[PDB]
Amino acid sequence: QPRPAFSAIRRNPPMGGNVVIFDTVITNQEEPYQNHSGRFVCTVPGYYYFTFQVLSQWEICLSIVSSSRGQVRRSLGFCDTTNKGLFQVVSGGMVLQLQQGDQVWVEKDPKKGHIYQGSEADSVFSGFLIFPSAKQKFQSVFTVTRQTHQPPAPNSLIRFNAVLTNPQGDYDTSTGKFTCKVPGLYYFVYHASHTANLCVLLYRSGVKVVTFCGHTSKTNQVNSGGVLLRLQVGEEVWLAVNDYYDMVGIQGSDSVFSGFLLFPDGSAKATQKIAFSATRTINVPLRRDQTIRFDHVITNMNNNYEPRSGKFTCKVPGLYYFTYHASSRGNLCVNLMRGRERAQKVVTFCDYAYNTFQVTTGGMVLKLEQGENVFLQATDKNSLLGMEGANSIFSGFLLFPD
Ligand SMILES: [Mg+2]
Image (cartoon, rainbow, N blue to C red; front, side, top):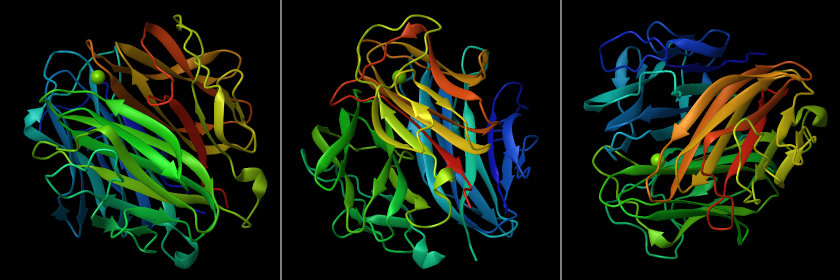
């Protein structure tokens, strides 16, 4: 069984060109990613998820581009134009259906291309196979996007009117809702561009699950959020806004919503359906080197996440994707940790905020051995909020169960 999955970061990247080269490989199962060029190469045709979290201090606009038969296919873009010298993370992601030989990479706008260079924090590009193309009725995947210059109405459901992929029709662009056909464990994630305050709320069958808010005046930022949910047939999932409703991106900064089935109910081996999502609801100030506890479990299939510590511990060796979204009111750096009793830093994600509210994100594909821990660790920059209406969440799931 193919297991194509990678993550790479920047450390000593080659200079020049508009392709963003992530030169330092963290994970590269089947070696599809080329660290000398920045390009992922598809061997196994199918549906893949790609995502990036890139650190800037000025203006940055990025886009996930692909090629087929060497013909370039431009796509959505994501920008942060805060432009104040402080760490900002721009994020974006989408499902892509690929053929053998297709390539995928991140490109910067030659006019807005500032990417941090140094050791204080990291930028990451990740991708992994979701479903091989070879089934389709028993899969579920979508990436949809909001193509309009007019923002949603306050306190309303966010309609994504345009489809990038939706092969089962599980997202309905005329209602704005995803409806479950194949019951099981799903990942949902969004990246929404805005130039005024924006809160995005994710609903499941009429109940608010998580909320993430980002504040800005005039300049463009990306609000991100996501969660793993175990759904039954007929359940609905959708995004909405509250009184903070702005989704007006600048030119080149779009808004996307994706979801995909990871583990069907009643298929394969339950011991390998491993996924967790947990939020933080305690507001005690963190101290440097403290493990960040996410105490409230939304999902914890096979109980490999420990909410009382905040640590994931690997039972089933394999490739895992870890991700978080943290609300914050000041400067925040988090170390992503991997190891056993003595854990080691994989990356640090920093996102600074001056007298405002932010949501930041990071993610990583990691190969894990039985017994290895993965968790988030606090630094001296510890502004982290966890509350209804500004959540912080930590999630992880096994790639390639059966
Ligand atoms: Mg920020």
